């Protein structure tokens, strides 16, 4: 992910 | 301080987690925080944010262990299946030791926990142990007896193997092979 985590 | 709307996200997840799940958060961040946080667990995430160690990816990992795929969609808009592939890389914000114990407990069911206790009686000799205590509780229980150490498990693999849980045993092996973290003061 990390790309779906940045959501914050 | 610093206001930021990140506080709101942190506050919302605390309310959603059950008291049972809330315990896991303390356990997982136990290494990161020496229980310096006041009695309220809400403050636990708050102090982590101040340290800057609070990554969103970590939150996704934290919510996943407590089996809260539902909250992932609402808070981080993360797909449940995405977590499975994402965790494939097996990334850990904190030492895998703490997470390893939490993850294994999650895999084991209520029946498995009871059976595990009987095996522990032979080595423990019938110490302060009961079916009431959860798997997570069992992990810290062994710490008192010093039967299990971060760099030496051995016993954990044997008992789990008896329960015919090869997958759990395999995961533990990864941890043992992950000792070369090169982490020191």
Image (cartoon, coloured by chain):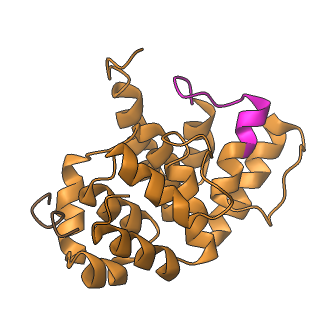
Q: Is residue B81 left or right of residue B46?
A: left
Question: Camera-side residue: B72 or B14?
Answer: B14
For this orientation, the residue located farthest to the left is A3
Question: Camera-side residue: B12 or B80?
Answer: B12
Q: Main secondary structure of the magenta part?
A: loop
Q: Which color has been applied to chain B in this rendered view? A: orange
Relative to B5, residue B28 above or below: above
Q: Choose top left, top right, bottom left or bottom right for residue B21.
A: bottom right
Q: Is residue B158 left or right of residue B39?
A: left
User: Magenta span covers which residues?
Assistant: B141-153
Where does residue B8 sit, x and y in percent of width and height? Answer: 36, 75
Where does residue B67 sit, x and y in percent of width and height? Answer: 43, 73
Q: Which color has been applied to chain A in this rendered view? A: brown
Q: Is residue B77 left or right of residue B161?
A: left
- Is residue B108 visible in this depiction of the protein? no
At a point 63% along the width and 44% down the height, the residue shown is B159
Question: Camera-side residue: B7 or B151?
Answer: B7
At a point 54% along the width and 66% down the height, the residue shown is B42
For this orientation, the residue located farthest to the top is B185
- Is residue B154 visible in this depiction of the protein? yes
């Amino acid at each position: 992910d990390f790309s779906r985590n940045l959501y914050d | 301080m610093g206001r930021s709307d990140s506080a709101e996200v942190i506050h919302q997840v605390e309310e959603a987690l059950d008291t049972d799940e809330k315990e896991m958060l303390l356990f997982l961040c136990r290494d990161v925080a020496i229980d310096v946080v006041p009695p309220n667990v809400r403050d636990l995430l708050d102090i982590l944010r101040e340290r800057g160690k609070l990554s969103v990816g970590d939150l996704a990992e934290l919510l996943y262990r407590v089996r809260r795929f539902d909250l992932l969609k609402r808070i981080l808009k993360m797909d449940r299946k995405a977590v499975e592939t994402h965790l494939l890389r097996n990334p850990h914000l904190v030492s895998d030791y703490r997470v390893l114990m939490a993850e294994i407990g999650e895999d084991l069911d209520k029946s498995d926990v009871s059976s595990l206790i009987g095996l522990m009686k032979d080595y423990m000799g019938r110490g302060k142990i009961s079916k009431e205590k959860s798997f997570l509780d069992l992990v810290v229980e062994l710490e008192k007896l010093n039967l299990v150490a971060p760099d030496q498990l051995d016993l954990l693999e044997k008992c789990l193997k008896n329960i015919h849980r090869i997958d759990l045993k395999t995961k533990i092996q990864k941890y043992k092979q992950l000792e070369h973290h090169h982490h020191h003061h």
